[PDB]
Length: 71
Ligand SMILES: [Ca+2]
Ligand SMILES: [Ca+2]
Image 1 (cartoon, rainbow, N blue to C red):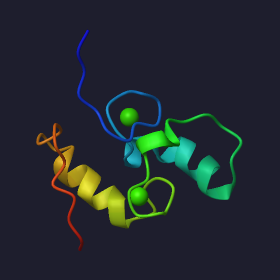
Image 2 (cartoon, protein in one colour):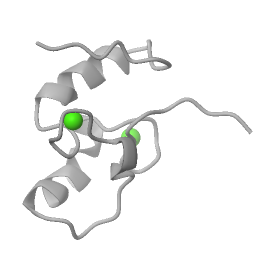
Image 3 (cartoon, protein in one colour):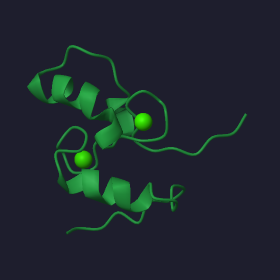
Image 4 (tube, protein in one colour):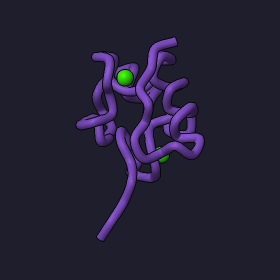
């Protein structure tokens, strides 16, 4: 009916360290199944470290818009 998430791995909430498991598998190659659709936002794939941060940064609670920023 309604949900808020952007770039989820296991469609839990978002792609972060928590989804590092599927990440390691994804980083190595494309074998698993993840919502890579809107998982990448810097042509990386998911969260190599640049997004990971912004993720744990916005996913902290702001999870709704995600103030995508560099750092
Ligand atoms: Ca998740
Ligand atoms: Ca990314």
